[PDB]
Image (tube, rainbow, N blue to C red):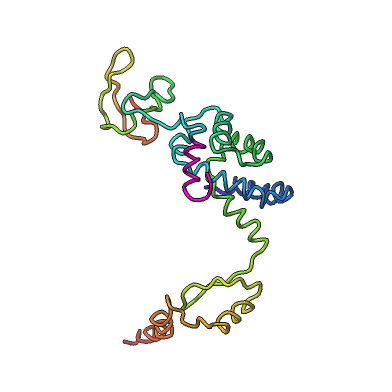
Amino acid sequence: EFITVARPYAKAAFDFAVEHQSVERWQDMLAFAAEVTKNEQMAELLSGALAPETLAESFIAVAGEQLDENGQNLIRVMAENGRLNALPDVLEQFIHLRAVSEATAEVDVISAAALSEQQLAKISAAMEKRLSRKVKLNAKIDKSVMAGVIIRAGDMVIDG
Amino acid sequence: MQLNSTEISELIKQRIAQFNVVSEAHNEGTIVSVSDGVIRIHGLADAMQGEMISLPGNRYAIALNLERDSVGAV
């Protein structure tokens, strides 16, 4: 969960992986791995194991070894490191690898969520709300917005 | 295995590739890791803390306190 060890990971992920294009390919392999630790017996059995060799062994082995050899010999790398203990850190950091690479997004304020990928501000944003259509903001629609301006307002009711 | 809970299905058949593994003992278990008679404790996980426990060859191994994973004991 340090994710910094996994930072060096996701580093080597875009790096060797995307270099191998395993950023996607071991996005697949990686996916299967988080599936492996996701196995709770494989969690229940996660660490009793002194030999990390035993771990990568029963790991690729158990799970079905969808990891690359970059991830099998890397399975020696992190498994041996035992930093393999934390799967998702560099998984969301790899999601941050390809995704950060691809980043365009949005966040709905005073609205039900948006997340419309906007490479630029207001780019897909004003295009979305303008594009609304939706325009309802349903989650945060009214009480949230009207309590936003009226939030500032009660903030004036600070005068009491 | 594949996608939902198949991930856990043939992670139980991928497990079950390996599935001989996951298990634990209470008490039973073992003294996980030790030097000089204080031990990380393996197995025996959930137990009354400080239950003097029939100890090697003899003693009632005095359960020190729950360090949840591997209890230390006297």
Q: Which one is in front, B6 or A55?
A: B6
Q: Which residues are magenta?
A: B1-15
The answer to which image quadrant residue A96 occupies is bottom right
- Residue displayed at 49% across by 37% down: B13
Rendering coords of residue A24 (x, y %): 66, 52
| B65 left or right of A12 in image | left
Q: Is residue A89 above or below residue A59?
A: below
Q: Is residue B35 above or below residue B24?
A: above
Rendering coords of residue B11 (x, y %): 49, 40
The answer to which image quadrant residue A53 occupies is top right
For residue B7: magenta? Answer: yes
- Residue displayed at 67% across by 49% down: A25
For residue A111: magenta? Answer: no
| A160 left or right of A25 in image | left
Q: Quadrant of the C terminus of chain A?
A: bottom left
Q: Which one is in front, A9 or A23?
A: A23
Farthest residue toward the top? B57
Rendering coords of residue A7 (x, y %): 62, 49
Rendering coords of residue A62 (x, y %): 53, 35
- Residue displayed at 55% across by 82% down: A129
- Residue displayed at 61% across by 81% down: A127
Total residue callouts:
0
Q: Is residue A101 above or below residue A6?
A: below
